[PDB]
Amino acid sequence: PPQPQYSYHDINVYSLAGLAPHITLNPTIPLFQAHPQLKQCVRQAIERAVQELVHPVVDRSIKIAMTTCEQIVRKDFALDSEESRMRIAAHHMMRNLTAGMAMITCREPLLMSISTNLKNSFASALRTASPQQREMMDQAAAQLAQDNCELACCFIQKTAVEKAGPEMDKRLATEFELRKHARQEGRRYCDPVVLTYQAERMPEQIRLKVGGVDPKQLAVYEEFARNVPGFLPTNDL
Amino acid sequence: AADREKIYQWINELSSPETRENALLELSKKRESVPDLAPMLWHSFGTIAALLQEIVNIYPSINPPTLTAHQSNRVCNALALLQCVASHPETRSAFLAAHIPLFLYPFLHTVSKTRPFEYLRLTSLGVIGALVKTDEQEVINFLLTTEIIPLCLRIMESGSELSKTVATFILQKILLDDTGLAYICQTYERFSHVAMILGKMVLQLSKEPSARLLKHVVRCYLRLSDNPRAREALRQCLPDQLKDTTFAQVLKDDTTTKRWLAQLVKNLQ
Figure 1 (tube, one colour):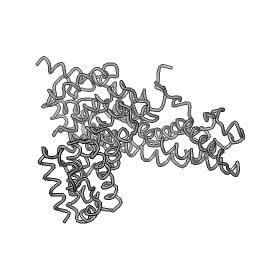
Figure 2: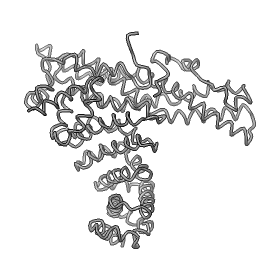
Figure 3: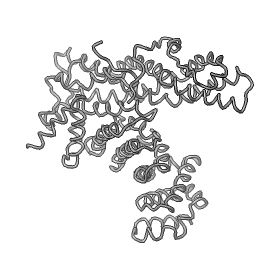
Figure 4: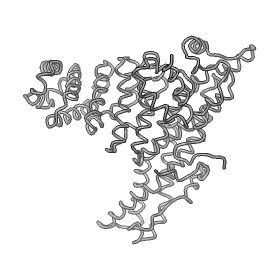
């Protein structure tokens, strides 16, 4: 039932400053009712959680997504002598699967880390602590972590997506080389193994075309670009 | 050739999100009457990418756990198609090379006890199950680098009887492989974690019989006793329920498991 809160463009990721306007502070939080001052330490605890997790999460997500995306794209575009369609589709799929892996990877570590940061901030500023105020503290840090996890994740997901594209480009350099080499010897690239299999074993109705991929068959890959997990889908503005 | 042309059309209709849900349903029903469904799915354009799309698109519903019955039914039709690909001699290796099981691990990691999540987990387990049934060493080697053992152990402890059974069977296949036995027995921490979980399961089985689950638990112990270090630790920590007559009655039909239990005891001398 719940849609994502942000669009891809709603969050600028060039700097950790992009996080501040979106941070949400439930005014009913008991710890906040008692010391409205502690609201001041939230932004920095969040920014430091993101700062410590962004690069491991980005690195791991791209690494998981890379192999899967390279193999499938290589497979789907095997009889496609052009490098243009392949590059775009690989772009869309890689960016999408990376964002998904990023979302799966950082959520629970973000919760833990944001909660930990807030408590320690809370416990240092005010001041001193108390058996009924540490309960407000841990209530506050847990709920705030929950309330800000989507924003923190989105930040990290977007960082991963921006980096993913050029990594896929580098990974597919030889594929682009195969198609470029062939054109210079005056011919279309066609994977010989795939050409044979498709011609001999695949039913006509579902065969990869030597003669090209019907624009309708590309619906999957367009959808990867349209609908990225953790963000509002794209439209015709 | 009338019903087969019906299959080609659903396959083509998997690419577009407008016709995909329906094609998922219809194809998942036909997979025991279409022997070559797997290479057709694998080798057609955009199909595997569409199934992966189905998987990744429910990631937002995983955490926080808001997955519905309908969402779960839909993605499980996709998973059912992928299980078909994991089983087939012609598609297994490429399925594995594409690392597709990794996009299932986020499902195996969920802990929500609602039926949409339990079905999700069971169906995901079924894909890994299909893989190890083939008895390929390549499969085991992939599973060992990808850390599916802790995932399986958590499920063996807390899942439905069905999920526990599939998860234990996966562990069993890994153990039966020489590399898998060595890996799990490589450190006391690893071996201890596994033994501890098997011990808990044995206790739970003594209160609620499951022939199938008990069989796989026993096979795991038996295989563990092929390792000299494990054999020594098992002498000390083997559950008493596996030594007395706790399970005699549920086993008198199952000669195979009886025989296995018998050799386990004999090995520990």
